[PDB]
Length: 98
Image (cartoon, rainbow, N blue to C red; front, side, top):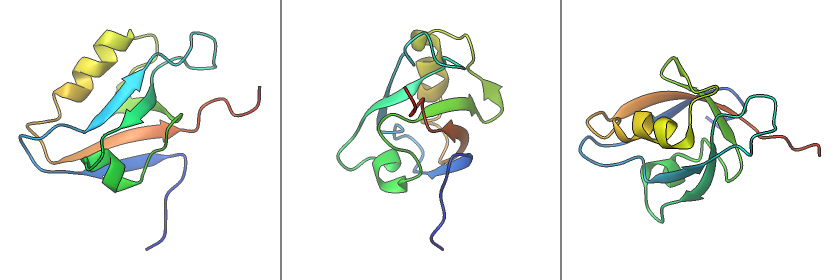
């Protein structure tokens, strides 16, 4: 049961619906500037999943590294998960020390 830490995350949602989550540029400066959660929808899949947190970054999406990819792009790869229910994404607590 109780389990969830910087690693392989699984967001269980329903098809047709969005990931109900907003992402933003990982402040060009951190180790791997990909993308981090800027805000969570009040009743979305991500907010309910509880697998991520405001500030955490995504290393990849279902095996699709976002390293280097622009904020606009990374978002597109996340917007195409609406047609799917279950999605796998790698999360990594942003740069806490600093």
